[PDB]
Amino acid sequence: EAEAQEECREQMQRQQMLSHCRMYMRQQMEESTYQTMPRRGMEPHMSECCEQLEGMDESCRCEGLRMMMRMMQQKEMQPRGEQMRRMMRLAENIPSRCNLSPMRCPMGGSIAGF
Image (tube, rainbow, N blue to C red; front, side, top):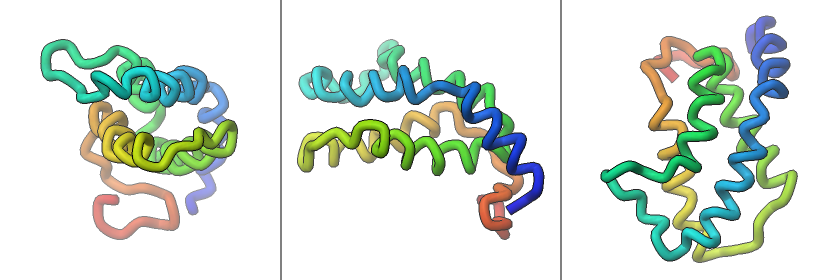
């Protein structure tokens, strides 16, 4: 855990992506029909949160998802087994879209390219 972690954690507050992100979860509920992300112009809902990570420092991005993921469920752990289960894969895809060759993640002093 690098001392610069504070910069990351602090910035996370600014990155209030969880608001739109939370909306995305709800969107998943309604989107339960079309949830399958189409190549032709993907859903903007996901893109909304994408900018936040994308705007968040790379090293901070690692901690961001971890903190946000836990915070998301904590804020309002949506109740759903089969439905949300599918969302899991989609969830990882959201940050993939903004993901970028990460050199090192100060999250527990990663070894390889986290």
